[PDB]
Image (tube, rainbow over all chains, first blue to last red; front, side):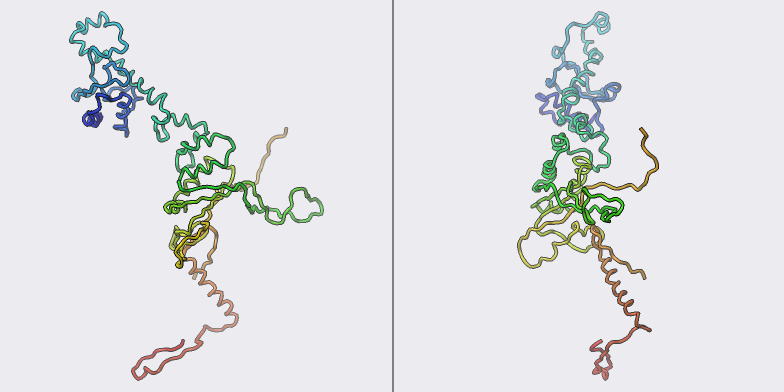
Amino acid sequence: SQSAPARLITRYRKQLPYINFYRFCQLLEQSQPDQPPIGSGWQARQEAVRFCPYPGMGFPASEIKDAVIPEESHLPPIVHVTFMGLYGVTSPLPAHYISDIAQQREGHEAAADFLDIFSHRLITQYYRIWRKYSYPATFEAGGQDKTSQYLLGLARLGIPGCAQNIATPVSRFLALLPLMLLPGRTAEGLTSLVTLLAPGTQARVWHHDRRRIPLKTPLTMRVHHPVSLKSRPVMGDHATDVNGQVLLQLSTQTGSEVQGWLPGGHLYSDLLALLHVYLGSRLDVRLQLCVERSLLPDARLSCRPAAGSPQLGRTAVMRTQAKIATSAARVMTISLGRYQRVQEHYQRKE
Amino acid sequence: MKIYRPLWEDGAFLMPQQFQQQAAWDVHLADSVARMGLAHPWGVVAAEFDDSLLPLSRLNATRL
């Protein structure tokens, strides 16, 4: 592009005696990254690219130092430094070609344009291995869920295609990937999920808790004359099932994050990080919070009255200082149902 | 008219349009209690006036 030297070499002509070639080609694609002259499109369409005047120098890596860019010939690379840069050059020119350049003379100055057509298309991809195609360390790639070193390095958790139903794409690989490689585990990863997302907040887990209802549809405590059973099913009218409904508390001390956990702020961060990434249909999770008194108003219209289920933060017109309280509840991270129906067919008679 | 009952479900926030509906319902419950003993619509329990401003012609009450 015309903007590629008009940004770089017209303004930044102060470190070109000691610049790296590794650094230089990176800033070209960072000069116009919006719809860039993609280096992978070399395979048919090097015409109309206007790339940088590296080639014809015959230089190794990090030894491009000379800085001359024309503007009239509509393609900036026309460079041949004589007596230097013979990188891999062994024998002189053939017999019939010297008879057309006549005779390895001043006409050779207009011959290396065609002659270095081969070295132009190779030092593109020579660079591309060191920086994009086998190195990038998921750091020189630096993508936004496009760069292939992410997708090669994230399918070992089993998320291709499963970005569906998530309001964000897969971004929390940076810390959860060591934790998300052990199977069937754990409880202590939920501490990392909170300390990542908002510091100043701590987490404690109680493994079992007194869950309640599920109301059984036959009451089953009819005392039966024809047939009944004893061995396990003994109860009253509502059952209790402990087995899988853990309790989680949070504890903040910066009031800017207190208004982040009430629904709308950071509650959408946990509610999608659990349900499809770390737990899924393993368990159900209960949330709770403990702060000092509140910051909560009252009966204003359509939608933001409720501090979960409870209300407070409005009545103390008496005393100066603190009392600690539990805050509220948040909903479970559950997903269930029955669908409706009765059936019509069967499996197989074997 | 149309007089509605509220439902105090958990996870149902707060509207001041609700409390007006419930409070204008036991008033309707008061009539169905009372209309088992009534012919014709109601009247005056007590009414007292102050007649001092009659020569300066004005009329104002004391207890009503």
